[PDB]
Each structure stands twice: as C-alpha cells, then as structure tokens.
C-alpha cells in the first residue's frame, strides 16, 4: 500500500555550497504508513514513541493577564541556557486576552515579553504554573516598527527568535519584525513585510527582580531575496521568520543562522520536480508528478534557510542556499533549530497537519532530520519519515481546527505547538487547544531520547512523560 522511502546519506557539504536536502513525498508518506487505526475509545493513530502524552485539561495559565505562546530561554551561541545572578529568564510572544481580539487573531498584536524565576529549584518544588514572574514588554513601544521605515501599515508585530547573552549591552535579541497593511476583514492591501532583526539591551538583576535597558536601536538583518527565499510579491501568504543564531564548531570563525522560508517561486507555479516526490521509477506506490501538481500540492513549498554573518559584530548577514525543502509536502517548517549530539547535526522544525500538501498527512508537532553537517543530505528521523513528536492524532479522520474541533478527531490533536529542544533533549512548548479550552500557556516540559536516526518520547520522565508546566531550566550561570 505504501511507497519505499527516499534514502538519504547524511553526507555533509560546504555550508556555502549549492545543495538542498529534500523532505520528499515518499519520506513524508512514511508517517501514515507507520500509523494504526485507533482502537475505540483511543483516538491516537501515531506510534506511541512519537506521541506527546495527553496534557491535563485543567492546566494552569503561565500568567492570568497575558496570552503566552512561542517561548525561548536566555542562551549563548552554543545553545546553553543561562541563569543571570541566580535567576532563570525566558522570552515569549505575548498578547492581551481581554483587548477585543480572539486567540487566533493573536499574531498581528504580538509583543516580546520576558519572565523570570529563582534558579536551582526542581520543577516539582515550584508552583504548578512554573512560578514565572512577568516582567512586561522587552522592547520600548515604537522601537521595533522603525525597521520598516515610512510604509503603509495598520499593524506591526514582534515574532520569534533567540536571546544571545554576549556597548555595556550583554543581550542580543534576534527576532522577526512583521508589518501588516490589512482591511478590517484581515485581507492584505499590500503583502506583509517580514524582516529578521536584531536589538541589543542590558539584563540587570538584584534580589527582588530582573529588568532590561536598551533595545532602542533595531537593526534589519535579512528580508527575503526572491532567489532562495520567497517574497510577499511572489506569495502574499509567504513565511519568513524564526532566526536561530548558532556557532558550528566545524566552522569556528563563523556565526550562522537557520530560519523558516518558502521556496522562492511565484504562487501557483508548477515548480515541483521528481526529486520532491522521491520515488524509484519502479515503486508501484509511486505518484505521477503532474497528478501531484494538479492536486494543488504546488501551494506547499516550505524551506529552512541558512545565513552567515559577514562582519565580526554580526550586524551584517548574507543568505546561503536553503538546507531543507518540503516542496509539494508541507508549506510550514517553522522554528528550525540546529541541535548538536554525538558529533551529529539534528535539524528540528515544527509543522502543522493542515499545511500538508494533498496526498500527504501527519500531525502537528516536531519534525527532525540528522546529518554530518549544517548542510547535509539530511536523514528524516524515525523510519525516514521526519516525524519526531506529534500531538495525539487520528490521521484516518479529518484534522478540524483549534477553533472548531472535529468531534471524530482527538481533542488534543492541537494540544501543543512551537516545540523547542533544550539541552539533554527536554522539549518546551505552549498549549493551543485542549477540547473547548484555548491555552496561551506553557505546556508541560517533555523529554525525547535522541538515538542516531530515531527518537523515543521518554515516558519515565515526570508523570508518564509530562514534566513541569513551562519548565525551561538554565544548565549554566551567565
């Protein structure tokens, strides 16, 4: 019934070289191949080892005054999570739950906030909610939007990136600034503008609180080129965001960045090739290329981009060819991260069931690939499928939506999103929808065992796999 997965070597290339690993239809079709029809009253089709445990429906809010979603720690370029003066510090996308707009209209209102808590306390000794103290907006009002200059706009938002502890500034925040020009119906009057940007500030603390100064000067670093990375002009619905800045010890003088993009094509272009399908000419379960494009799969054109700093100050950056594409497979490979383990390079990226191309299916959650370098013939994890950890999902019934759950679907198919892989394979995420309840709160922290080309969610960790709500611990003092 199911096709032979596209094989991959994991072989490393020069980071500057023109080679892009393909997350192929033959690979992605492995996810449903590995699935089982759920046995009532169970509603999960995924392998148990690739399934996030059920989050309790009585979960606490991270903060009752703030919607919280995509979250990152205070870090260095190695990926270490740092306490500062005996505090743990996190940064979150933030919105107001009592301001007129509904949770799914969060995005255009997003402000980067910070939270803090005393370090060196085991999760099970903290308050159930993780004990995060909300410090407020990280950036001064009006500082971020200066990055767009004098352009027509109705909204601007601060989206995800990273905080690097490093001019008696000591924190560089890499994030995505986005500008919208929308009619009241949410229609684009002009295409959204998405600029990966940097703001530097100073973290300070005493015994009572953490606070920040600076972040007045926002530097535009990268906008899509329309050669490697799709622009608003090519596709008003383009994705360009989620900078992950890191050091590769294979390239000691360099600073790199992975990010979410789309394959740089005009929307509706019949641009998919045999290499995106990834079949043996002899596979009896192979697809026809034109048939795949006719099914509308040409609207799913995810890539993970790579950029390299061109000055010592990391204020100037250059695009390199994309390191992964999911053309005719999925439109979204979000929050890409490079995770170094056992001398290997893991690319983790988050994706959605509802952004899969026709004829391909998989859950919301974390996808993973392993290689010998940051530019590899990346090996999709777990039976050459790419699935690392999915929300419990029946792939034999419709997806529905977090704002309108299909009754025949697992009510936790949207339970978590924006999974971030921390040192020692701990995974931090936010709650979207659990049955009728919307989250905007941090999920229980979870643990994946990363073993070569496969992964197991650790059901010995915390309570049957679930650790503390919003448990984002520092491994090193700053």
Image (tube, rainbow, N blue to C red):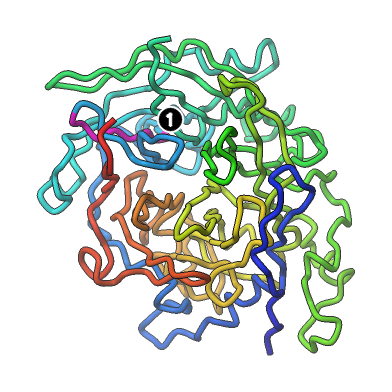
Residue 468 x %, y %: 22, 53
Residue 124, placed above or below residue 311: below
Quadrant containing the N terminus in the rendered view? bottom right
Query: Where is residue 312, by image quadrant?
Result: top right
Residue at the spot 75% in from the left edge and 34% down from the top edge: 232
Residue 409, placed above or below residue 301: below
Tell me, yes or no, whether the highlighted magenta stretch contains residue 313. Answer: no
Residue at the spot 62% in from the left edge and 77% down from the top edge: 30
User: 105 left or right of 424?
Assistant: right
Residue at the spot 81% in from the left edge and 81% down from the top edge: 280
Residue nearest the viewer, comparing 470 with 353: 470
Residue 359 x %, y %: 71, 72
Quadrant containing the C terminus in the rendered view? top left
User: 291 left or right of 429?
Assistant: right
Region of the chain picked out in magenta, as a range: 86-93
Residue at the spot 61% in from the left edge and 17% down from the top edge: 147
- The residue that mark 1 highlights is 164
Mark 1 neighbour class, 10 Å CA radius: few under 14, some 14 to 19, many 20 or more: many
């Amino acid at each position: 019934g199911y096709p032979i997965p596209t094989p991959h070597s994991g072989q490393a290339y020069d980071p500057f070289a023109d080679f892009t690993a393909k997350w192929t239809r033959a690979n992605a079709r492995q996810i449903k191949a590995q699935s089982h029809v759920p046995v009532s009253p169970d509603q999960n089709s995924l392998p148990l080892n690739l399934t996030m445990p059920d989050i309790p429906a009585d979960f606490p809010q991270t903060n009752p005054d703030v919607w919280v979603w995509d979250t990152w720690p205070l870090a260095d370029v190695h990926g270490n999570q740092l306490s500062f003066q005996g505090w743990e510090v996190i940064f979150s996308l933030t919105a107001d739950p009592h301001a007129g707009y509904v949770f799914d209209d969060r995005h255009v209102h997003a402000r980067i906030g910070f939270f803090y808590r005393k370090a060196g306390i085991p999760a099970n000794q903290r308050p159930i909610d993780g004990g995060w103290i909300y410090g407020g907006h990280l950036f001064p009002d009006g500082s971020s939007v200066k990055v767009f200059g004098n352009v027509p706009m109705t909204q601007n938002a601060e989206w995800s990136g990273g905080a690097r502890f490093v001019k008696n500034n000591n924190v560089s925040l890499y994030y995505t600034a986005t500008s919208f020009n929308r009619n009241a119906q949410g229609g684009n009057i002009t295409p959204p503008i998405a600029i990966i940007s940097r703001a530097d500030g100073q973290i300070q603390a005493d015994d009572k609180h953490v606070w920040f100064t600076g972040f007045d000067q926002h530097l535009p670093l990268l906008a899509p080129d329309g050669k490697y990375y799709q622009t608003g002009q090519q596709n008003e619905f383009f994705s360009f965001r989620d900078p992950y800045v890191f050091l590769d010890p294979a390239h000691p003088g360099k600073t790199f960045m992975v990010f979410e993009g789309n394959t740089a094509v005009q929307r509706g272009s019949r641009s998919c090739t045999e290499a995106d399908l990834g079949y043996s000419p002899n596979d009896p379960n192979k697809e026809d290329l034109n048939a795949v494009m006719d099914s509308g799969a040409i609207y799913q054109m995810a890539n993970v981009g790579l950029a390299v700093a061109t000055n010592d100050e990391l204020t100037q950056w250059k695009f390199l060819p994309p390191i992964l594409s999911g053309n005719c497979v999925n439109d979204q490979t979000e929050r890409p991260q490079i995770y170094l383990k056992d001398g290997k390079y893991y690319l983790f990226t988050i994706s959605r069931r509802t952004t899969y191309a026709a004829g391909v299916d998989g859950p919301d959650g974390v996808y993973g690939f392993v290689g010998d370098g940051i530019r590899s013939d990346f090996i999709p994890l777990n039976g050459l499928s790419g699935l690392t950890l999915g929300n419990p999902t029946d792939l034999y019934q419709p997806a529905g939506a977090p704002y309108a759950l299909n009754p025949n679907q697992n009510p936790r198919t949207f339970q978590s999103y924006s999974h971030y892989v921390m040192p020692g394979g701990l995974v931090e995420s936010y709650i979207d929808a659990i049955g009728p309840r919307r989250g905007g709160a941090l999920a229980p922290t979870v643990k994946i065992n990363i073993n070569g080309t496969s992964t197991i969610l650790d059901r010995t960790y915390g309570n049957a796999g679930l650790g503390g709500y919003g448990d984002i611990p520092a491994n090193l003092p700053a």
